[PDB]
Image 1 (cartoon, rainbow, N blue to C red):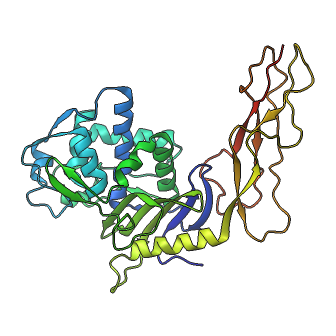
Image 2 (image 1 turned 180 degrees about the vertical axis):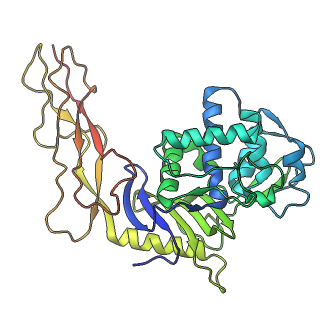
Length: 369
């Protein structure tokens, strides 16, 4: 299998395990996919409390004018003051650039400061090959004089599909709420109706059962790009397709390509349940040094699944409970007492988009002393 896109990568959301890749490390233009990094700082400000969903946000000259004549996906904002939630919805659903900019100025005072924030955030995540000059994903030539100091006039943000995967993963894992927005095939923006650019959602042309994200992006340099997330066959997959080959008879090539990528993933990988909730994966105990002494049976207290290729000579060694060494009492039933780690030997690409390999907590199913 090969994808009809210049660059792409697919990962299982939870573990960040790589399922498919094609030139996933070369930084390239990502257009509006940029708004994901943007939206992460917004939720982080909502969480910190500095802003709230109903907080009124002014819309300055720069973002406001950008909407009267800038063939930049936007929506009327003649009231120049909208809710954080309203802009958030406008940003993720319609890719409105003035929505993005507005939120940025609200959070950092200026798009520039906001960019420094997104540059810092990326470095936190271990992404050190990114190029961020704006919060929208547009090309600077579209921003005239409102470009980052030092940036070139035709510069564009750049991230690798690998990098994007990380971003998408961190966002979904830390702020699952975002899905309640990207999910909507249409919403309301202070009265008028906005339409999603994601055509794989409910009631849309390129619908594919399970989808509910994440962000499209199109630019001459970025091509037809789309970050999509979905739950297929019980597994959450994050998809990044960024530069779908342009097909003349299919405006939805980026989604077709994504749908194509998922047919591969679902027929190639599956989630085999290894441990049942309440049970123990190898009469598996963890030390306590005060009461009973021998055992706590450390047990799964949710069902544990692992990604597995289908067909593979005998299978995986996720045998492994370590404890965390022999601990004091009393030990309450339910407390974490060890971890089951999957020693994955079927690494695709760099294997994982995280330096951590999957480990699931094993709980104590009895009290001691």
